[PDB]
Amino acid sequence: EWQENKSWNAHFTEHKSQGVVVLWNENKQQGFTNNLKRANQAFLPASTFKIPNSLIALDLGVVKDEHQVFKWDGQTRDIATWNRDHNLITAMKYSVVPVYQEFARQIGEARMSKMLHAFDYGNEDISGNVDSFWLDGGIRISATEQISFLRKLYHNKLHVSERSQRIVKQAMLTEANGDYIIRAKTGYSTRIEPKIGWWVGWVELDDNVWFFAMNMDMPTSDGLGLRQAITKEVLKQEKIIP
Amino acid sequence: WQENKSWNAHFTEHKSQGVVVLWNENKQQGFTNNLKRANQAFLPASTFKIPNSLIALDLGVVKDEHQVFKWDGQTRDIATWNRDHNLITAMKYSVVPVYQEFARQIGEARMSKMLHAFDYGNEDISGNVDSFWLDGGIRISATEQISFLRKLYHNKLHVSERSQRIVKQAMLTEANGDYIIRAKTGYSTRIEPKIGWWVGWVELDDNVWFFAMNMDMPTSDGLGLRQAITKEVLKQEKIIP
């Protein structure tokens, strides 16, 4: 069950933003959102797709491990951090699209589609073709669907090996300290309206895990840090993090 | 294997005595303030939770990082111990009693073989099966810790890849956009000299810096210096901001 807490809207309002945050309390098997409607609206996953894309690439052997280097092709792209060599960890961290497009090509459309279906991932539509569908094709996923997917990953219940899932959860590591561990993935969908930012993942506490998936309208790149800030503004309000 | 005696200031500043050892994985170069003490072997104390975890996982004594180890209802000096734990929280709170139970279940034969297979320190588990890393015969130097950690990082220890991955998960101490630290503290109080340890590594985008430090720890008061000193050293070396 899901509970709407419209008070979280203040965190969007304060930052002159519109969006949804969805939380799931694993112990209590309860979910919370500021906007049930938008929680169930599907959007392009953009770089959040790196999570399933990694799982599949690892499981098929397209990526041997998290150390394998994927050389910069020497083509300066807009994003400075992309113009360097990468492995899975840093490719995830810096959302290095070109690396994952190459994975997607090597995976191919048949295996990609089968695996997404096996994952129950979003609308499971990769039209098309292989190497951009999460950016400007047909694949869409809602925040509540992201939670469902993430929960399976956390529990190693996705239809790939345990190793693949552990490696991807490693690669998702975003922040940790004595109070919490956040494993998550950002996304930024720009190719198709509405432009949105994502942050999906979970917060590991000593005794519980809180899954989250947020997206928000992102008319310009200026607002990208709000993905995390608003999520954390909500996590703080809910005493999940200090 | 450079000695940089300038890092001694980081110990002197805190009226402390100790050693920090760094290993730059890419350059295959090590650095320390004190080559002698870098090679001096001490009780590992709770840094032993790293190999103890690996062995427990690999033998099935620990099924996974979620398995709960119920508190035995004995209230001890450390509050966080007086509660149920899994591998992650047991490592985080250095829950000795949990790992003593693992050690008992592992037993002396398998413990000894495994430490040899790990090339771990002096590989000597003389003493109580469930306390030898606290007050038995096992000794390991900072440089030996680095050697062991390097094998762990590369999944080259003689246990399954899964075991090594889980323990590296459990070692997670700190992460942000600049670095990840996977590490384990220790505090050897039973047998003189009382020392504190911090051993692990810092993962950067491009490189991994292994570290192992220990320092005299006459009282618990100084325990935060383990991390503080290591981090000022890391900061001086521009490894972390």
Image: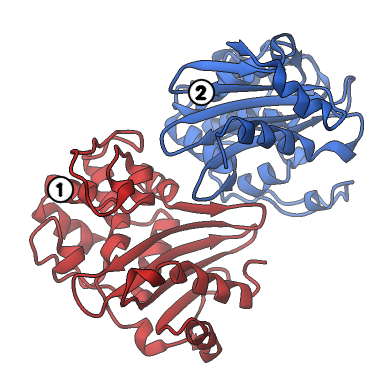
Chain colours: A red, B blue
Mark 2 closeness class: few <14, some 14–19, many ≥20 residues within 10 Å: some
- Which residue position holds label 1? A107
Give x and y (percent) for residue B127.
Answer: 81, 17
Give x and y (percent) for residue A91.
Answer: 32, 46
Q: Nearer the viewer, residue B229 or A232?
A: B229
Point 47% across, 16% down: residue? B28
Please, what is the three-letter code of the amino acid marked with disc 2? Asn
Q: Circle 1 marks a residue in which chain?
A: A
Total numbered circles: 2
Point 49% across, 30% down: residue? B208
Q: Circle 2 marks a residue in which chain?
A: B
Q: In this view, does B136 lie to the left or right of A75?
A: right
- Which residue position holds label 2? B24
Instruction: Give the Cα distance between marks 2 and 1.
Output: 35 Å
Quick check: B140 above or below B76?
A: above
Give x and y (percent) for residue A237.
Answer: 62, 78
Report whether residue B19 is seen. no
Place residue B116 in its image quadrant. Answer: top right
Element carrying mark 1: helix
Check chain identity for marks 2 and 1: say if they share one. no
